[PDB]
Image: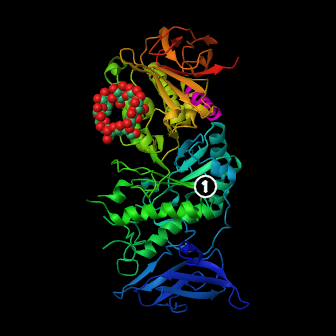
Amino acid sequence: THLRPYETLGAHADTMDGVTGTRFSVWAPNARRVSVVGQFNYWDGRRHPMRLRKESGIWELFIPGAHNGQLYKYEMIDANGNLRLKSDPYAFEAQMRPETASLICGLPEKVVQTEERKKANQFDAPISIYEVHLGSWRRHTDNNFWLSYRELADQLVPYAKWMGFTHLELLPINEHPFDGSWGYQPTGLYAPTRRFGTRDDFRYFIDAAHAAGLNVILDWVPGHFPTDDFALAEFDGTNLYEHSTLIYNYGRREVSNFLVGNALYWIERFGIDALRVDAVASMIYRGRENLEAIEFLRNTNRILGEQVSGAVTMAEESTDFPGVSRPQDMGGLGFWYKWNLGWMHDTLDYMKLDPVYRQYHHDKLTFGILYNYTENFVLPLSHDEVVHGKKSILDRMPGDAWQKFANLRAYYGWMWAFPGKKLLFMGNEFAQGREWNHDASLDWHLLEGGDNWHHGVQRLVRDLNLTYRHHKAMHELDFDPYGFEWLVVDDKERSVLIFVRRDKEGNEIIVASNFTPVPRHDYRFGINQPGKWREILNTDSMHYHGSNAGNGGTVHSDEIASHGRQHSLSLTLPPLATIWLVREAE
Ligand SMILES: OC[C@H]1O[C@@H]2O[C@H]3[C@H](O)[C@@H](O)[C@@H](O[C@H]4[C@H](O)[C@@H](O)[C@@H](O[C@H]5[C@H](O)[C@@H](O)[C@@H](O[C@H]6[C@H](O)[C@@H](O)[C@@H](O[C@H]7[C@H](O)[C@@H](O)[C@@H](O[C@H]8[C@H](O)[C@@H](O)[C@@H](O[C@H]9[C@H](O)[C@@H](O)[C@@H](O[C@H]1[C@H](O)[C@H]2O)O[C@@H]9CO)O[C@@H]8CO)O[C@@H]7CO)O[C@@H]6CO)O[C@@H]5CO)O[C@@H]4CO)O[C@@H]3CO
């Protein structure tokens, strides 16, 4: 089968006549002479040469004795007669850095995707994603050492679960030489990085997240050609993998296979539930449409949908290509979800404003609804927004510290109610003050000592996650106009916005935000479902170090017309706060 080349190519365990060893395979159409230099070979390129079969362009050889755990490389004479030693491109495990040898290990057992994890990826599911860079989430304190995959299984997984997230999204765990690329500049697509342990350690981590009831999304980097360690370029002396600045030759059948293969591998051999492709614009552009890139993405998506249904793909595309998360049969790219960068830009510009000026930019909060139904959106507060002098999310907020925290609380309240799934970068849940530093631990010291405003934000994010998951109105109909309706879309003067989220049964949750520090008392607005209403979420609660203003129990609607509706509520709206209300059955 052509889809799963990692099941044949590379180093696997084989049984050629009683004797055991490993069979090596490499694809290099126009090289001449390739030998296998391992640990079993005293590292001698005279002892073990490979026999090429020219129909496929694949060299191969079976070596008895050669067992799992042994380092190895390929010694190749390239088209030009140069001696270069190459890493196996299908290295399933790579030796500790510097170094670049591959390790014989073979494949892990296939992971079957469970019904409850497939359900967890569906469009009607509450999806709240904790985005993490494994190298900088936590460190050991005395020595500043990385946490291993296994320590991450014992600390990060329980933390994410308790905080009420449904998904853990990982910056690329591909093998990569430079910590500073964050994993986006890989050298070994099929080996999880050795920074945190072995490939079996990574697998234990994935297993642990699943046992805790978490789906795992992996950042997958099919758009960043390896540019380090002569790892993939001019692989056999010619432009094997890359186009004739370095970029994959997607239209070339085998290359495409190498990449679609890689997706299938993470999902099938590691149990990953979803992949995210960054920087899609620079795959499809940079009239300038790279037609081979567009068809490759269309293809890969088609194949995953047929082969591993239940798994999903997500995309970040920054030029408004139409139909990124739409079906290929139409103009689409075939992704299930798209990052809503426009929403992130508009709402942050809005929150940055001195509250006194927000009346003039009401547009920034109401625009998201206009194009909400063109893509299946994730609302993202990602690692890219908290580096390079962009500041932390907290530090973007205006005012003295206490006003900053209140603005940030009100904003999360808004984000968690607004149509679209949720993604939050580590550090944001406890309002880290400093920018993200991939070479240090996050600022957990902020949570040391007596209860403070950072604990307050952290409780709020948990309550938001648990509330968002419990009520279907908040998540069931994000991508259906029936799921959302403005109750007060034009109170610009006071910067009060009020809408309703709705589930399939037609139950409504009312969402109200007051984006200025003026408290509003007896604020009357029209509603759709008369009766008794009660707060289920209040970002000004003392439980989060707010001032504890609010409605103080059940409020009954009145038969007094408002905003073209026949019944209304008259509520207190706390300053710099958002509240959610539910209707009580009688
Ligand atoms: O081709 C690209 C699309 O965008 C282009 O839109 C341009 C406008 O035509 C142009 O006038 C101008 O608009 C800007 C405007 O000047 C600013 O003031 C501001 O608008 C704000 C507005 O003032 C606020 O009130 C608020 O709007 C909310 C609205 O008040 C509220 O009721 C609700 O709206 C829903 C309606 O209740 C309901 O009727 C329905 O309306 C549908 C429509 O019936 C249906 O045909 C649907 O199908 C298409 C649509 O026709 C297309 O036009 C397409 O948009 C493109 C335009 O053609 C471009 O010209 O979108 C739909 C595809 O799904 O369109 C309507 C939307 O469903 O549903 C409404 C939505 O629920 O919610 C709104 C939103 O909160 O907020 C506004 C602040 O953003 O901003 C305008 C943008 O600049 O410039 C536009 C250029 O982008």
Q: Residue at x 47, y 10 (%)?
A: 520
Place of residue 23 in the rendered image (x, y in percent of width and height, measured from the top left)? 60, 83
Name which residue type carries label 1. Answer: Gly
Identified at 52% across, 33% down, the residue is 482
Residue 200 visible in the shown view: yes
Where does residue 243 sit, x and y in percent of width and height? 33, 71
The dominant secondary structure in magenta is helix
Front position in the image: 115 or 520: 115
Farthest residue, direction right: 18
Q: How would you rate the neighbour count of disc 1 (Cα within 10 Å): few for under 14, some for 14-19, many for 20 or more? A: many
* Element carrying mark 1: loop
Q: Which residues are magenta?
A: 456-470
Which residue is rendered at x = 48% and y = 72% of the image? 257
In the picture provided, is 117 more to the left or to the right than 235?
A: right
Q: Nearer the viewer, residue 385 or 556?
A: 556
Magenta residue check for 458: yes
Note whether residue 193 is visible.
no
Tell me the quadrant of ligand 1. top left
244 above or below 218? below
Which residue lies under the disc numbered 1? Answer: 310
On whether ligand 1 comes within 8 Å of the CB at mark 1, the answer is: no
Relative to 452, does residue 470 appear above or below in the rendering?
below
In the image, residue 155 above or below residue 33: above
The image quadrant where one finds the C terminus is top right
Instruction: Name the spot of residue 51 as percent of width and height, x first.
Output: 52, 92
